[PDB]
Image (cartoon, rainbow, N blue to C red; front, side, top):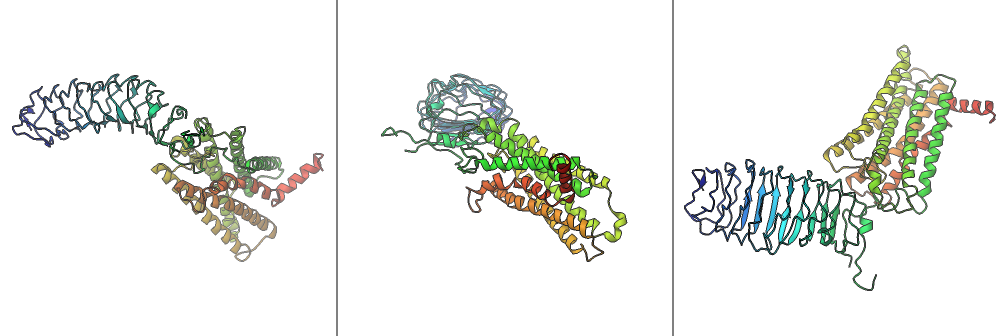
Length: 561
């Protein structure tokens, strides 16, 4: 109760909660009127922005303290708590204290006591010896969503810390190694969403459990020699599981107390990206074959005497997409190359930087370009053959060029979408955009899948219409129409048989649903997914009359034949 904007209660109360009442200052040591006190929580008492020191005089039996929604509190004076041996809970929420309060004047002896600071965006750092002479048995520290930016070395003395928590501490940058020089424990620590560069060398050596989910900055972890009792761990990088999967040497000089999360589901294995017993060289062979085929197709297209028609433009776009996919595969193989199978403590330098981001952007751009090229090829036959009776209204090369430019722009936008931050390409070993950890990323993945399904359905409908109207509707020209239909069907089949199962497997992996198995689920995405880069050019060198004629002419003229 607050009278004249000050404490004026007249009846002894223990579990009284501070509700909306007239209060602006807590008198110093004038807390009379209450003989036995259990908990005094000020949540709807934000009018009392400033409280004088030594407000609690003889609150020996006080159990819980919770100040919430007191944003108007500019700062907390030293010696807020004086006598409270039976203290069991303390929490400060939403307070706008620019300086860390001096809680060293509180004397208590309890083991279940927990001190939590939350919703505070004004605290800069925890000063040294902040909790000096506060408790004698155990303290549980929580900093859920605090505004602290750094920590001070040796910021603990005269007390034992059972566990620590720093969840949602995005403003925090780093903490000194010797931050717990004179501290005990902690048994468990939390660094989730803390943006900590590295764990402290001292104080954390006795940590049994750790939490670093969504840290996004824990590229370095302590050596396994220092952490000899890590009972559990939750690291957002699924690469330390293999290095930390060591049982303790309890007896016989070599019990599996060590643990990691997430488990090694083979999505980011300790070995190379594609390194298997015999499938390591398959990726390299496929990449070389695709690169050679794309180079040959590009050379034939550039050196072709005839003008680049709309089917020729579509073939050139498909060859460019295949070349981009082959270059991405070659870069991935080179990254996997020379690792010698020890690529477990190496992904930190792999995903971080512009490497995997560029690889994922290139892969997305190649996929979008291939999809748009297939759609354009399907749509071209829907008007030239079906609408032959209106052949005078046939589209010109300018329209095809504009369509190709629009498709390239759409592919570039799709590739740049995860670069801004919509999706993360660092969630896979192959460094591809298969992250569903965010609502925006899931929405983008669903939209991409829907667009791919719509494009496939449109291509199938256009092919069916072309086949139905090839000769029945108006007329049929055997040579040109047959060649165009054969090339379009070959390209559509090569794209579908290499993308649709791959897309379904990638969607299942992102959804974390094992459809058949988790071992070979990524095998198709690693090997079967990019084969369309090489399969398409191979069909392009045996089903294109102009390309094969140009190749034969070059071979005969330029000394080859």
